[PDB]
Amino acid sequence: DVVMTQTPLSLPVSLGDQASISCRSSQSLVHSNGNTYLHWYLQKPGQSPKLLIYKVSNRFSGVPDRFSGSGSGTDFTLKISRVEAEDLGIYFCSQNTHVPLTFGAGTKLELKRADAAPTVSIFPPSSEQLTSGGASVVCFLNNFYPKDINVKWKIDGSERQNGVLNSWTDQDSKDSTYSMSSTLTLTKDEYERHNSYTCEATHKTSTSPIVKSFNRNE
Amino acid sequence: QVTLKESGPGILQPSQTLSLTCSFSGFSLSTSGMGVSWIRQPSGKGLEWLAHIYWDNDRYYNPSLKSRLTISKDTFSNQVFLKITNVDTADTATYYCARSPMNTWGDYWGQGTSVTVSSAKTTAPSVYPLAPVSSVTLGCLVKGYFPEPVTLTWNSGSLSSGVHTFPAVLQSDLYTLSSSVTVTSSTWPSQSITCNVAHPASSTKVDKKIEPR
Image 1: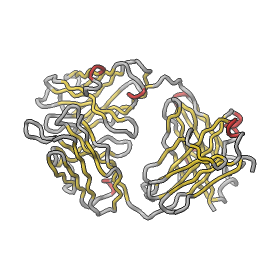
Image 2 (image 1 turned 30 degrees about the vertical axis):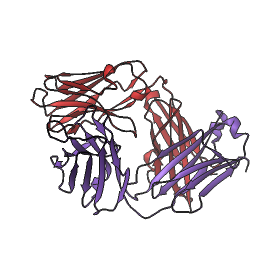
Image 3 (image 1 turned 90 degrees about the horizontal axis):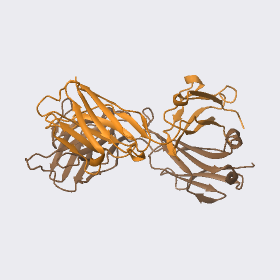
Image 4 (image 1 turned 90 degrees about the vertical axis):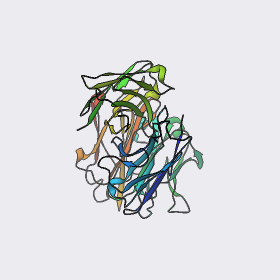
């Protein structure tokens, strides 16, 4: 298949800035009929893709002149001038010169804001879950920026990777931050064999991780 | 105006046949050059094109799935169909149909239809209150349900500010989600905070009050 390599994957920008998105194909997208079937689309959460540019550089109906496409052969660029809030979303390239039709992985155009450290909260298993025979430990890491974060779970000071479920929110429409939920699921017998439970958050706002812990008996 | 609406079964068991319908308006598959494609998007993954049909019944398929796919149309009814045989968990995705004439492939997309392929049985969630170990953060853990979705509110929807309801994640065929709520210390525990969780598929509605430990 024709592989479409889209960069960057994440593109933070300020409103009014220009954003540039690159799409490189594994082989030329020039069709035998002379046309180049490279398109650009914008997709928002819970919405379907909307066509912005067709055949490299043609704007589709209703698309503002701030969107412009360029390139040829295997190298293509979408430039968005004077970015507005309604432009934020995922952009992707597609090709239909070759079967199968293929797509780039997408570029998330996001709003840049000041750095914010996550607010970290840890929760032991509820009495109801323990009665049921289970034990989940939850950690919320809320309202941080940039989006890049790492969570490490430790049981009695030892790193635990298995049984971790992570979920992330989309950038907040009001404060432009991100939030994350991390759940460590253990058996109740495992929970009843260890004392210390720790959520450690590594983020660009601190050289040392933010550590939230509790002791099962304290 | 051009409009497209996908319809499907919602949930299927592995090995069953998926039958999708694209009902459209504002264009005709009798028009020279007109075509329609099917594309799918598993949650948070890449788009995958499936098949295409033109007004003259020229049909194209994704080579890796061709033996499992059949695209067809009912021109007078303004409908396009896709049949996918022997489905498995990897066929879980949102399925889109898109108007795709010769010069402008995929120029108008439908809003999609969600398809879940699973052998899981309808399972109501276990709802657990998350009380803590200036401001206080409480939570609600909604664990082990099938299928999606659940609706989660705080104080019957009256508590909406400072709420983060996270997307569900799959674990051993069941979904789990969580929600956090942050209120001032003078608000809780002096005032009641309850997470309300409804799972229409199991016809359940559970209220879990957050109590101090």
